[PDB]
Image (spheres, coloured by chain):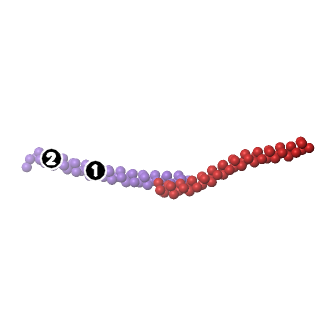
Amino acid sequence: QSEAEKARKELLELEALSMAVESTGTAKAEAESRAEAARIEGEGSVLQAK
Amino acid sequence: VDQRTRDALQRSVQLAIEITTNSQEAAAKHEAQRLEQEARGRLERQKILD
């Protein structure tokens, strides 16, 4: 079990990176989709007001 | 001098052979468990490396 835990720490150190990529990619993808729509709607709103 | 006394000693011989037979199987059981655990511990480690 001690030999398994030496190896398991390295697996957990990799899963912490996989979980950081999956969480940041999901959060970034949604926020940028809102920021793009809000910029298109904002530039359009300047012309509509004109 | 009496056969009834030789018969009592003849039972002691059989019990001494059974004691030796049990001692052999108990030793095989201990090495089987040692090897089984030695294989199992390496397999548990390899799953974490995979």
Residue under label 1: B21
Label 1: how many Cα within 10 Å (few below 14, some 14–19, many 20+): few
Check the rendered structure and report the hue given to chain A. red
How far across and down, in percent of the image, does residue B12 sit? 19, 49
Q: Does dot 1 land on a helix, a strand or a loop?
A: helix
Residue under label 2: B8
Label 2 and label 1: CA atoms lie apart by: 21 Å
Furthest residue in direction right, as rendered: A50
Q: Which mark is first along the chain, 1 or 2?
A: 2
| Residue that appears at 69% across and 49% down | A25
B12 or B48: nearer the viewer? B48
Furthest residue in direction top, as rendered: A48
How far across and down, in percent of the image, does residue B38 sit? 43, 55
Q: Does dot 2 land on a helix, a strand or a loop?
A: helix
Is residue B44 left or right of B2 when viewed as pictured?
Answer: right
Is residue B10 left or right of A31 when viewed as pictured?
Answer: left
How far across and down, in percent of the image, does residue B4 sit? 11, 45
Check the rendered structure and report the hue given to chain B. purple
How far across and down, in percent of the image, does residue B49 sit? 54, 55
